[PDB]
Each structure stands twice: as C-alpha cells, then as structure tokens.
Image (cartoon, coloured by chain):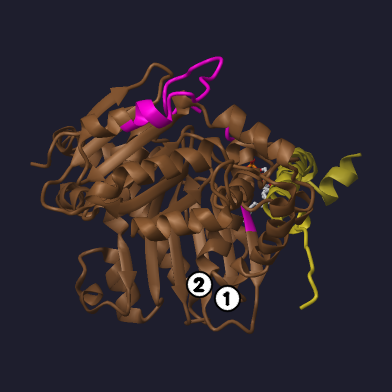
Amino acid sequence: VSPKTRTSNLKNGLTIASESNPLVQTATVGVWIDAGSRNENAYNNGTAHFFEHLAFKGTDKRSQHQLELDIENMGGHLNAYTSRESTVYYAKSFKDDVPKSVEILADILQHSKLAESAIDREREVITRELEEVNKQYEEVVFDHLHATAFMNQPLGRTILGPRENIQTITNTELRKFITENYTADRMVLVGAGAVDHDALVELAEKYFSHLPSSQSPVPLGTPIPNFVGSEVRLRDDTMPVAHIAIAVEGVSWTSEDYYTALVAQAIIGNYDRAVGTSRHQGSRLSNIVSENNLANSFQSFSTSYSDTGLWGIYLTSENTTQIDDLVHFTLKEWNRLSTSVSNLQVERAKSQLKAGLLLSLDGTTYVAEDIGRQLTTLGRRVTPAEVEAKLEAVTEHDVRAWAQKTLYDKDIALVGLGPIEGLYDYNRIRNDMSMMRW
Amino acid sequence: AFLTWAAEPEHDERKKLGLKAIIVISAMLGLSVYIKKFKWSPIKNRKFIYNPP
C-alpha cells in the first residue's frame, strides 16, 4: 500500500498534489497544465510547442546563460513536453534542491522574456524539426493517424504546426496563448519522491500566487470530435519495414467504458520478436504472429482524450508479402472480442492489468506523471483500491457489449508507411471488421 | 387470333411472367448501381499529394 496522495489548493485555484517516498533521495516537482496544441486555432497552430522552446531562452531576471548555469548548479535537470491536451514542465533534483527548482519553474512560466531575437533564432530550429521527425516512423504514423481520424478538427492538428505558422508566430500571439491557457485553475503543481507536502504548498504560495485565474473556471479535465473512417498511405518501397496503424474511435478519460476498453486492449496485448518471452505469450494474436513470422512487433493502444479516444494497434513488419495475412489475422482477433470472448480471456487480462497499472509507476518521474495526468484529466488521483474495484467490475459480457458497439463492423482509420503494396484497399480491410459466419 | 394462339399457346402466361421479371430485374439493376457506387467511392474519391523525393 503506497502512501496517500495529499492535495491542497491555493486561493487562485492552483492545485498542489504530492506523494512522498522516504526511501528515495531525489524529487520530481513540476507543473501539469490542462492545455496543449488542441487549444490553438488553425492560424496559431504550433504556438504551444513554440513556447516550450522559448521557456528555456531566458526570463526577466536570468538570461539564457544564467538559466543554464542555475540548473547546472542545482545538479538535476529540467524537462518539458507539449501534447494535444496536456503540457508538462518538471524538474528532477536532490531532496534539498526542491525550493530552487520550484523557483526556476515559476520563473520560466510566468516571467519569460519572449524576445524577438530569440523568436527569430528558434524559428529556424523548429523549421529543421519538421524535416527530422520524418525519421521517427512511429511518430509519423501516429501523427497521420490523428490527422485523418479527426479530419479538419483540432485533435487532427500536429503539435509542431505547419511551416507557414512557424514563420509567422509573434511574441504577441505567444503571450496571448500562455495568458489565456496557463491559468491557475488549469494547473497542478506536483511533487513526488523526497518532498514534504506542507513545504511544497508554501513554495506554491511564494511563487505561484500571482497566477491569473480564468474568467469561467471549469473543473480539471473538461473538454465535438466526429471520427472519420479513412486511410493515409505513405508508400515507400525503399524502406525495409512497413509501419501500419489501425484504430477505431475509442473512449475518453471519464468514459464508463474506460476500463472495459483497457481490458479489451490487454486481450490482444503486445508482441516483439526481440523479446525472449514474446513467443510464449497467451494472446491468440501473439501466437499467430510469432508462429507465422508475420511481424517484428505489434502494440495495442487505447489513447484517451477529454471527449474521445483512439483504440487500435500499431504493427511493424518486414514480411512484405504477408501484410495481408497480418492485417487479416489482427482484425479477426478483434472480431472475437465481439463474438467469442468469455471469462477465460477476460479474467486473464484483468489479472495482468491489476498489476500492470501499479508496475508502471516505478520512479519519482513516473509517479509525478501519474499524479499530474490523473489530476488534469479526472480532477482527482484515483486510489489503487478504486482502480482494483473498477477492473474487477469488468465482466466478459461488458467486453462483448463494448466490442459490439465500438469495434464490430465499424469504420477504421488506417495509416500505412513503407513497403505497403501488400496492404489491400480500404474496403477489404474494413470488411475484416465483421465475420460473415457470425 | 385463334391460329396465333395455336402457334404460341404460352403467350398469355409468358407475358405475365415477363412483367414480373422486368420489375424484379429493374429493381435489382437500380440497387446494383447503388451498391457498386457505394463500394467504389473510396477509389473514386482518392486524393494524392506528391512530394518528389
């Protein structure tokens, strides 16, 4: 039984959430923000990512060089990432360097220069990032997957934004973005590891007290996405490995089917030919794929957003003449979530997940990420006892009902990259979403 | 008239069955057009973006 997550608020509406671990010597403190690229329109798309660069370019007090030195002197590091719905800025340090790190984070978020000279400098760095993501195949595949599934909608936009916007982002629109979005009621200060909650609350009162509150304070993790069945083919015969993602519209964080969808995902599971144990996994798809050498890997996912999600699988394969078999057998295993699954598969997947949801949190950064994610999506940290009860409530017959309304005979979003000549047209893929025998 | 009947005594039945066939086949032709267009729309609607390597 892990120590209890303590939670306090400030007057502005900033949440402070902490989980202490007296066995470790480091601490991850940071700011989780319920805001990301999805909050941009088409004209300022890329702003959130642009700001992440300039946050480390110097403040009203410390210059870029002074900033570098201050963190070097602390001994730990700072890190940041911007997603579609979430922005994170954290600092890993020593136990007694926590007041320094909170002070630096408060500075870069509230009091950043955003000097025209630095905007102009980063504008090239970010332009170069557009031509180097091209190598990260998984990211290419998932960005096209969002673009097509949420065609012409805010969730469909990339985080980097178009080339055109990068050239036209001003300090004015940067300032406007962070003033509108980085408000106290949307922010959570998180501490995990060697942190005292009461000390962290005092540091929040000292540094984050003059944060703006939004005009209309909605609860944390408050949002209509209209999924498009569609495909993107990025054929490249010179690549040796095909990368394919297939997804349906999945579930939001607060869906009643959230846990049902996780169990369904665990029934298919993951596979990697490079891992020794993968040939012996219980998953039927794993067995088919390994015995027939159909793939190098597959990874089931159930990605959630505030008001929608994507549920599907990501495949990589060198077997270019049997892509058809790989996709065929994958979708036939999904069909069985509707037609065939019983207590045998469901109880097995529940066993595996009851541990998996706890295992994931193995370092202070993972714990902080868990507290921060849950507070910004659900408005609260869900205790392991509650999670164990929600998993236990999932029956085989919940899974069947969920798959019958979510997967069975449904439109898919499909992205193929690489030597995908063997990937059949949309209809033949989508025809495998049902079984004529059932 | 009688001799025409003598040459083709199936005449009356044949034309009535033909009416039934015409109706069924016409309806099936209309439906086959809808179904073909439905199945073909992903191919017809396909769009390309080319970036020369």
Image: magenta residue range: A203-231
**Chain of the residue under label 2:** A
Camera-side residue: B13 or A298?
Answer: A298
| Visual hue assigned to chain B | yellow
Asked if residue A148 is positioned above or below residue A190 in the image, the reply reads: below
> Disc 1, disc 2: CB below 8 Å?
yes
Q: Is residue A275 visible?
A: yes
Residue type at mark 1 is Gly
Please state the horizontal and vertical placement of residue A321, each as a whole percent of the image.
Answer: 52, 82
Q: Which residue is mark 2?
A: A324
Which residue lies under the disc numbered 1?
Answer: A422
Q: Residue at x 54, y 69 (%)?
A: A136
For the residue pair A96 and A431, the one nearer the viewer reads as A96
Label 1 SS: loop
Task: Tell me the quarter of the image containing the N terminus of chain A.
Answer: top left
Instruction: Give the percent coordinates (x, y) of residue A312.
Output: 44, 53
Q: Main secondary structure of the magenta part?
A: loop
Q: Which mark is residue A251?
A: none
| Magenta stretch holds residue A403 | no
* In the rendered image, the vertical position of residue A145 relative to residue A324, given as above or below: above
